[PDB]
Amino acid sequence: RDQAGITGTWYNQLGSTFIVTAGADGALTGTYESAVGNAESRYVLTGRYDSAPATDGSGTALGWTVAWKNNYRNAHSATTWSGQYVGGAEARINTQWLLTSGTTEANAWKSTLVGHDTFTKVK
Amino acid sequence: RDQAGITGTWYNQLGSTFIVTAGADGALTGTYESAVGNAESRYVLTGRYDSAPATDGSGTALGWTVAWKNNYRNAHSATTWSGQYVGGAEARINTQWLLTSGTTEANAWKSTLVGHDTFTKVK
Amino acid sequence: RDQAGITGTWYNQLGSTFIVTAGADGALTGTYESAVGNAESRYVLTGRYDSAPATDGSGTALGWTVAWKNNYRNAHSATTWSGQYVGGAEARINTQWLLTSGTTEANAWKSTLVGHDTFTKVK
Amino acid sequence: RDQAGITGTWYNQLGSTFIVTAGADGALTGTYESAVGNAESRYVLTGRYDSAPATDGSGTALGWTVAWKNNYRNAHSATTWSGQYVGGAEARINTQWLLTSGTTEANAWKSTLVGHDTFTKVK
Image (cartoon, rainbow over all chains, first blue to last red; front, side, top):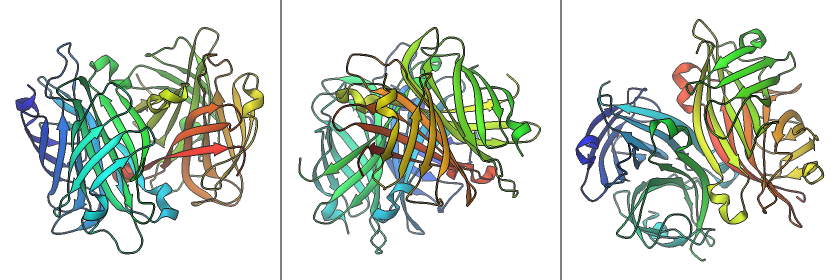
């Protein structure tokens, strides 16, 4: 439905690269490359999207996760993005995210960053 | 590593049921059943976890997504949980979550709920 | 310090109006008018800011609260904005916010919206 | 209304101390002492609460801010708590919070922590 609209290469305001395939079943698969933080090269992502969204002009809800471990680095952390895809000439994925680091129990109060990323099809 | 510790059936404070398998590669697969909201029965989830966490007593970072569409209902929304697994006698997964609904652009300011769920191996 | 830079009239991307005075002591006082939601006219706000920020080019941390009760309406809710003031030609206050509604205990999981507002000195 | 219920000394799960007065007009004034982080002794807080909440068993919405500057320390950061007061034998204030640090523009993606604190009248 928005399978075609979501599948592809997206870029956020930080210059990160989100490469995703949307499956007919609601699956999101792909790779993420962050332009910032304790990260290098590509990381696996997986997520889900609403494969039968409302037809009233609403966006398409979706989310995905990256664990920041690959063959190069392990930042002992994971980010989830929660948001919606908005189609059209200037298609966008508007997200908020939560980045949790593994911590000791004494430090768990400072485990989680929150922010917002907007992805577009052009950098 | 925490593959065995994470795999299984978890319950949160709302009485929701999180059934997950942790793969050797960092994958999370399974099903979620919410005790609240516009939800019935099981929904697909997918996520990621740190398969090689720190050995200094830190938790294990992880996250997952549910899109709230199944064969019974479609709530045009997705939730992502971001958190850490803490092993031991009283193992826990401590999370914060973001629930994004598909909205019109005019309503996007009110698209996203935030909360926190704690999962245990016993209800 | 940024007392002069913060004091004044600010506008966000929704067309809301934030009127604030920064005190020498770190106080924020003023009024908020939301262009959206269950709101009309001005609401009291109060908050705090860092009156002696770092001199290394960092922003100035601040926050404020609105309870959505005035002489016209009571939305049984409160929003807090947490963010930083960035000075200069295009001064900005970049925030994330939490909007909590009063709920029953059974509904408390869906009590809190999260979002992000960027304020500028020009609409 | 909940003026009497809110006014007083509260303690969270970290062992922090929140001392507040609720004014008839919806004002919150007081001091905060954090048991964790870059903090020592008391800090000024100000906030707002719904002075005429619903009478249907709903909680009372409120929020407050601390800027982490006092005569002893300056952590160049501010926290806002957004939540609701629930009255009764085991009265509670259930909150989520946003802690923003002043950062450079390049580091603003990692400026804001999110968490949740529950306050009770007994430690």
